[PDB]
Image (tube, rainbow over all chains, first blue to last red; front, side):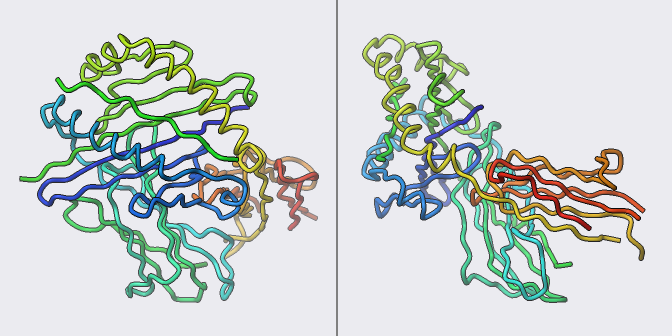
Length: 183
Length: 193
């Protein structure tokens, strides 16, 4: 019936501290086709099958990034450095699959409804940092111009294990976190 | 196939801080390529200041900030011809390039039926791993569709091009079936309990 293909790109910077970010990606319905790693000029497909079916010239994104960054400086000026209030994320933590003790699974941490799109996710098992095999998404857009982001932790369910996902949003006082434990 | 991109137009120039500027180039497809709409949105911070819609053929200011830019871009007929062409060289080209693995992407649901409780008060039908997100999950008691005591979560995005949903039946010779219809399946899945 209905489909949306989006090319979504953004260019942002902070002062105090000074930092810049950029993102260039293509999306289909709610899901990401690819993003370009702007430092390396590489198209990164969300699923490896996409990269076998299709191609994208990542140099094109780098040309867009130069235009994006110039646009940013012109719109900062045209707006007299007007700024918006930050919106802190809502977190959900849920497994990919039916939980069976000792069957490998994936915990998904979904940070939603935040702005600006600068947030880091940290995983913990029984209060200790776990990072092996973790995948973090790039920032996905919303109709309300807020963002969302996915993180994935491979795990093996066991009785009495607790997991936590903590998100550090740019400029927040500290992390917000959610816990999960199996059935 | 080699995917195409869309250029951004450039607006005219007229302690801690944060600035954001972005652009979204959207292709809306109804009955595939039969009806195609190109929309390009320009955003500053948390507000859209302007867009181009291929059905309109011109830039429209969405805020006072974009008013100058819409008129500046609207005064350039070659610039407007360029945007109107995006419907073909961006939207139609890209649809042909990715339809096989997006519109035609098909991933079968896995269906699990569990007791929840301490005595049984609820049956959970967990349906995981599917694409596209459109799905019908129904509970039957002795071949009769239940609705009254049925509670469904929204279909949840896993973010990896798969979706899941949970359908709980409140209930106390009884034969309960969770029936799942999905575009990936030639035949519905009947998970008995």
